Amino acid sequence: KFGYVRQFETHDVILPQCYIVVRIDGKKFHEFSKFYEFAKPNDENALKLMNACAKNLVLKYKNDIILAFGESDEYSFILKSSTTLFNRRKDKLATLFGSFFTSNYVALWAKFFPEKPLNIKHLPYFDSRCVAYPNLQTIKDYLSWRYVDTHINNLYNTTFWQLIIKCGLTPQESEKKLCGTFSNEKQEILFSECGINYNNEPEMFKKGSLVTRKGEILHINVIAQIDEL
Amino acid sequence: KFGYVRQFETHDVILPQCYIVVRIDGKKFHEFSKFYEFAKPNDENALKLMNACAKNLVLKYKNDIILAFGESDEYSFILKSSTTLFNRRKDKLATLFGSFFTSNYVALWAKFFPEKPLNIKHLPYFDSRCVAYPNLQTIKDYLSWRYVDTHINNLYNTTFWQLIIKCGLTPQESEKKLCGTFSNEKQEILFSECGINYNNEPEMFKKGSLVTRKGEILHINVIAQIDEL
Amino acid sequence: KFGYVRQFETHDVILPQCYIVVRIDGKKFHEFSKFYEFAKPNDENALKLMNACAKNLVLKYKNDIILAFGESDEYSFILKSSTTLFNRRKDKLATLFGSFFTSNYVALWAKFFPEKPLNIKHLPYFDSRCVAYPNLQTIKDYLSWRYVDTHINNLYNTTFWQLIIKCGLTPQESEKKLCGTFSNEKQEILFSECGINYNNEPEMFKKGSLVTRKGEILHINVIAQIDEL
Amino acid sequence: KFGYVRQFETHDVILPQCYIVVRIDGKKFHEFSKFYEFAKPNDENALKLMNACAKNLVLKYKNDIILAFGESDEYSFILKSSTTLFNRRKDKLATLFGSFFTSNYVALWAKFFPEKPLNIKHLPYFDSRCVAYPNLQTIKDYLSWRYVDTHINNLYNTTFWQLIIKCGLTPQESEKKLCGTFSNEKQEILFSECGINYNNEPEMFKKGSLVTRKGEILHINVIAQIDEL
Ligand SMILES: Nc1nc2c(ncn2[C@@H]2O[C@H](COP(=O)(O)OP(=O)(O)OP(=O)(O)O)[C@@H](O)[C@H]2O)c(=O)[nH]1
Ligand SMILES: Nc1nc2c(ncn2[C@@H]2O[C@H](COP(=O)(O)OP(=O)(O)OP(=O)(O)O)[C@@H](O)[C@H]2O)c(=O)[nH]1
Ligand SMILES: Nc1nc2c(ncn2[C@@H]2O[C@H](COP(=O)(O)OP(=O)(O)OP(=O)(O)O)[C@@H](O)[C@H]2O)c(=O)[nH]1
Ligand SMILES: Nc1nc2c(ncn2[C@@H]2O[C@H](COP(=O)(O)OP(=O)(O)OP(=O)(O)O)[C@@H](O)[C@H]2O)c(=O)[nH]1
Ligand SMILES: [Mg+2]
Ligand SMILES: [Mg+2]
Ligand SMILES: [Mg+2]
Ligand SMILES: [Mg+2]
Ligand SMILES: [Mg+2]
Ligand SMILES: [Mg+2]
Ligand SMILES: [Mg+2]
Ligand SMILES: [Mg+2]
């Protein structure tokens, strides 16, 4: 009857024998972490909750997910190249993982933050993406890339917010001080002038949250994913 | 450094000057509605909640949404043929609307169901799609199609469940009984044997839930949407 | 047995109810035309060959083509927004039109250039493209855009080559010479110094080449394609 | 000015680090070879024409092709997993090989068939396609799939037409006579009843036509393509 409109849709699928990354990146989590007054560069609970949602998800698809890695508002799920999940539908993959994740976020909020509840006008909601990785080397480098990303970001943010806190700086000059440095330089700027050793930093913050199937862990890259299969 | 993995993504975008439909349809909502013991054929609270999320979602993007229409676990949001929202990106449209709606559902569950709190192991989560409609007639027809679908379904399901309830039938001979029947025939099964008149069914069940901008109403297809532009 | 590799293909199609443009443009036609000594930026024979090919093509699909417009090495074919040809498929439409065209080119060459035969090492070969246009305006404007292009460029290159030919200019100072000018300014540069009038330039050069179904004509935009339906 | 129409085009490309195949299959080659009265089901000259074309094609892009394999009206060209050609664009790869090839066919037709020239109303034109293969296994299997199809088809069609030709059979009873047979059974039907030995059938008909870079060979699968890289 009016059914012909269904003609217009698109059911496109990810290429066979490719890994699938589904990545989830929270929308405006700058302002979102501002409103609920998160813990500044790093909120132990906010990050842990992310981990919770991620764990529940890889638990949910325990067969198709090799592992996951979370950063800020972001979390990444690796789908084995052989997966038939959702008949390899991009939309279904992305949207469904995202909704499920979002749903676990909202659900589990009460546990991690009895402090400040959700109000309404300001809510979490997340982006989701399907990315095709044809061979193992690429997935490995993808995962690495995220890991880099977290490393750099925590470094910069940490030595930035210490300067404001400890040395009383404004956002402008704390930036100029940090401009053009190295990884090591900032760690010195942390160690002497901010007076804090960066290795003494908690390990979930530096090296990011990596969920294998079930129980989850935090360390660098040694690719023993090579072994897990 | 590793950044070339971003080389693998796809930013594909809805063709310019096309109306957009972002459709949301809950996953495994049969099991969902069974576990929380929804009101079978129709749960007033459930549908209303759905409506709440919708109202908040067209509120959120006021500029780009013409209107929305909800059915069961489904909602359809129309975007204006000229919209730049999220730069016309399929992924972002779909996934973001999905997260948001979902987020809204889990938030407002506390409100609509003090009866049964959420547990965990059963959580609401929804699928999302983008569709591209090159002209007004098709988008119109689309909406029509949805409405038709809700009218037909509601009639079948209603005479089905009143057969089971009132006359104590098993699903099978209720199916074969209902098999190959017609409109007036179902409604006849309804009033005589099931002792209930169909026109007195709440309007929101029969004709579905239509969200215009801000507040929302429930009737058929008469295109007064044609006038609002 | 090995047949699974077939499952790797992609069957993607043009969104329904969109006019379709198929554009053909010959690769390296600068070097090509330079090799075969085409006449300056205007060769009656080459353009007539192109037109003949296109005439053959709209002859071939008389059912799906509204009309077609040639400029240089370019030819654009407008398929009706309703067409089901090749089931609306990109690969088939681009490559098949391209092939067909290329084949007619190479066929009818001996006709249009009995002067010089084809050699081998340099052969005509053409890029083809599929574009979707969701309504009338867009299509009209596309066509416009093309006609525009042919008109403008006919003027610029004409006066350029007269500056080189008649006035003995080198390209560089002919370019700085023509730089910044206007339409009638250029026509004057043509009329006084180079001794030719641009209104008597052949209407096929100026207003571009246009083929409706069957017989073909050259003028501007008066969109009388409006009526044909 | 009208330029916005260009914003409707589509740049979609092949996923990085995938072998590409460009396959070429002439539309309606049944009627073409019927019209030009080709040789039963194997025309030596037709095949070598096809071959010279593909050689010129691999010749043209010597950098990005591992090799090419032709069968009937078909030819397949394997592009290396790392290729940047046409910036990996679907449209350009398909249409360009399509057109070059078509051009080469029509050109070198003179050489291969001095017997009957091309006419007009019946002209060769070819469908072209792109396929992405994420790994060597699959590209190998692709090729295998092809060689398989040609071997199988050559036997079936050969004893088919020998049954028609020599024993005076009509297509129906040849079709049944051949129905459900095995390889060796068919070669029998060939040796006892049609009087011909399928071992002495020309290796270019049986084992297909394989172009490595430059000069080209006909044998089976022994993948020394593994070493050439
Ligand atoms: N305060 C605070 N913010 C966090 C924390 N974890 C993540 N975030 C926020 O999330 C951001 C991560 O980068 P983005 O995802 O690009 O920020 P975004 O603006 O929310 O996301 P987009 O709109 O997609 O660009 C940071 O700027 C933080 O503000 C945290 O533990 N504490
Ligand atoms: N009992 C009850 N069920 C509802 C209500 N609203 C929606 N539903 C359920 O939602 C379903 C709608 O159909 P689908 O969305 O295709 O069901 P689904 O199995 O969850 O979805 P998929 O797994 O993606 O195919 C119905 O079968 C209903 O059971 C309600 O108000 N009451
Ligand atoms: N000499 C001559 N050249 C022509 C004529 N018509 C078209 N051309 C050539 O066609 C070109 C038109 O632009 P393009 O199609 O972009 O040329 P191209 O660089 O060979 O094509 P691409 O590689 O696809 O960009 C001019 O540079 C001319 O060299 C003609 O009548 N005479
Ligand atoms: N007689 C003859 N036919 C050949 C030869 N080589 C290829 N063919 C034709 O090639 C065809 C291969 O299949 P297709 O190309 O799919 O046939 P088609 O109907 O012409 O093409 P499509 O419309 O694309 O399906 C066979 O039907 C043959 O008729 C040959 O050497 N001799
Ligand atoms: Mg973000
Ligand atoms: Mg981020
Ligand atoms: Mg559903
Ligand atoms: Mg449904
Ligand atoms: Mg060109
Ligand atoms: Mg041009
Ligand atoms: Mg064919
Ligand atoms: Mg074939």
Image (spheres, coloured by chain):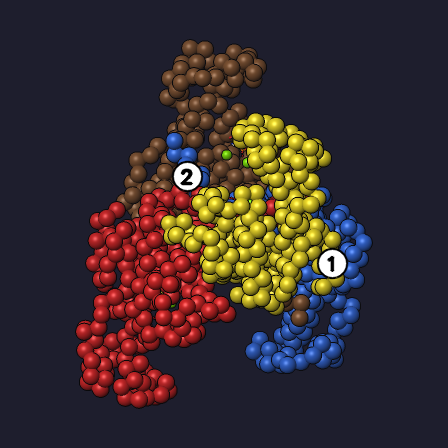
Chain colours: A red, B yellow, C blue, D brown
Q: At x 49% / y 68%, what residue is drawn?
A: A120
Q: Is residue D83 visible from the viewing direction of this image?
A: no
Q: At x 71% / y 64%, what residue is drawn?
A: B229
Q: Is residue A42 visible from the viewing direction of this image?
A: yes
User: What chain letter is assigned to the residue under label 2?
Assistant: C
Q: Which is nearer the eye, A101 or D46?
A: A101
Reading the image, the residue beneath label 1 is B224
Residue C90 on image: x %, y %: 57, 48
Residue C5: which disc? 2
Left or right of residue D47: residue A152: left
Q: At label 1, which amino acid type do we have?
A: Ala
Dot in front, 1 or 2? 1
Q: Secondary structure at mark 1?
A: loop
Please tell me if label 1 and label 2 are on a single chain: no
Q: Which is nearer the eye, D160 or C30?
A: D160
Residue A114 on image: x %, y %: 36, 67
Q: Is residue C143 above or below residue D199?
A: below
Residue C4 on image: x %, y %: 41, 36
Cβ–Cβ under 8 Å for marks 1 and 2:
no
